[PDB]
Image (cartoon, rainbow, N blue to C red):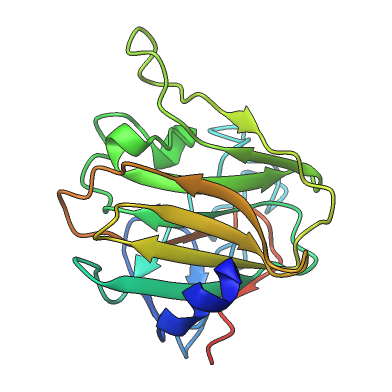
Length: 205
């Protein structure tokens, strides 16, 4: 029901190539993954190695080719076999340096970030606003996921200022929903493999 009504605003979303992420967007702009060329042709010795220069973080964030400033929008993302990824809605990477967001996965709605993430394979969580005393760290909240989602549906109601996440694999049951979102700027669909080499696609009806 709630998912069927949201599917009424199904839009064709295409990724936009940016020069601030190490992500790899397909030619059709309908698929994105992680890993970068051979190995950044840098090989700290063992090629892939384990970039300790900043390990535990790859920094691969991408947005949509079209911005959202009104009306409702809905699109699905296929994260099958993926052990980690970040998807939802973003207002851009304008405030990514000030709070080393992408660098330290500092996703926060106050920074223009309304997304959810999965890590380790079975660790789902929702990024929320964190204490100002520690601006370089978000308030990650663990989500109770019983049926690992093989496809997530994102619904955005600019007018209502809300971002919902549906579990297509779970009868399309609601996973999380951002309410009273500060939609004062143009938002775009956020996607992030999260070091995960497994590509995340966007169905498209």
